[PDB]
Image (cartoon, grey):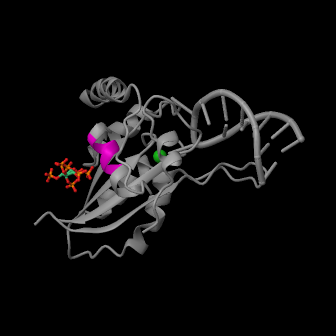
DNA sequence: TGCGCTTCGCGCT
């Protein structure tokens, strides 16, 4: 019901040029594997040192609203994240997501990242930790960009229009993420 | 608040 401005989407999910914030689109489906129950998007709480606030990453904001999703513990769910920056360890979700997957075995998590957030020195260990805890960790391709536009954006009937370099950036980042997860 | 560049801000205003 709450949809994203087209400009916000294309300025934040471009897999070639970064932004100083993170958006996260999310979908919950009930598993004989077909039921689409809760959808939305959110961004990080910006760091604001004038109020002495060190910020809250978008993935941690997703964990904050899980209670409000009212997932029935008698059902199995798949949670999908479309995140403009890969999750990280430092000030990140990696540890709390690991904890959240350990204590909630009825939840499967799938994470598609537009870009790799390597500004965290431990970003490799973060991605490896999420995989160890049974999360699927992937790079957004054309299919994921288009699904996100079709589902989360106020497109007003305008079909998704790929930016220049979309497939090239996707392949390069897929290469990097595979070398990280090979280890 | 808005700007200009843009790695979950910064450093001006
Ligand atoms: O593959 P189909 O079962 O024939 O239906 C697909 C499929 O629908 P859903 O995403 O709703 O399940 C696409 O996504 P995939 O499952 O193939 O990944 C979807 O694309 P969007 O999610 O981007 O909307 C696309 O929708 P459309 O063509 O109406 O834009 C639609 O049709 P196509 O397979 O003909 O592309
Ligand atoms: Cl994170």
* A66 relative to A123, above or below: below
Q: Nearer the viewer, residue A45 or A34?
A: A34
Q: Nearer the viewer, residue A47 or A162?
A: A162
Q: Is residue A81 visible?
A: no
Q: Residue at x 30, y 29 (%)?
A: A174
- Type of secondary structure dominating the magenta stretch: helix
Q: Residue furthest left?
A: A32
Residue A82 is left or right of residue B11, and the answer is left
Q: Residue furthest front?
A: A157
Residue B13, image x, y percentages: 89, 41
Q: Nearer the viewer, residue A171 or A162?
A: A162
* A71 relative to B8, above or below: below
> In the rendered view of the protein, which quadrant contains the N terminus of chain A?
bottom left
Residue A7, image x, y percentages: 52, 46
Q: Nearer the viewer, residue A123 or A42?
A: A42
Q: Which residues are magenta?
A: A143-148
Residue A97 is left or right of residue A132, and the answer is right
Residue A29, image x, y percentages: 24, 64
Q: Is residue A121 visible?
A: yes
């Amino acid at each position: 019901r709450h949809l994203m401005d087209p400009h916000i989407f294309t300025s934040n999910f471009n897999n070639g040029i970064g932004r100083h914030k993170t958006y996260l689109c999310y979908e919950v489906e009930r598993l004989s594997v077909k039921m689409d129950q809760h959808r939305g998007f959110l961004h990080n709480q910006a760091k604001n040192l004038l109020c002495g606030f060190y910020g809250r990453h978008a993935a941690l904001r997703f964990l904050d609203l899980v209670p409000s999703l009212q997932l029935d513990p008698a059902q199995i769910y798949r949670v999908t994240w479309f995140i403009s920056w890969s999750p990280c360890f430092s000030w990140g979700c990696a540890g709390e997501v690991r904890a959240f997957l350990q204590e909630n075995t009825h939840v499967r998590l799938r994470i598609f990242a537009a870009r790799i957030y390597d500004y965290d020195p431990l970003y490799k260990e973060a991605l490896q930790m999420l995989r160890d805890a049974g999360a699927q960790v992937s790079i957004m391709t054309y299919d994921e960009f288009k699904h996100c536009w079709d589902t989360f954006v106020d497109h007003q009937g305008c079909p998704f229009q790929p930016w220049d370099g979309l497939d090239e950036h996707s392949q390069a980042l897929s290469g990097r993420l595979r070398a990280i997860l090979q280890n």
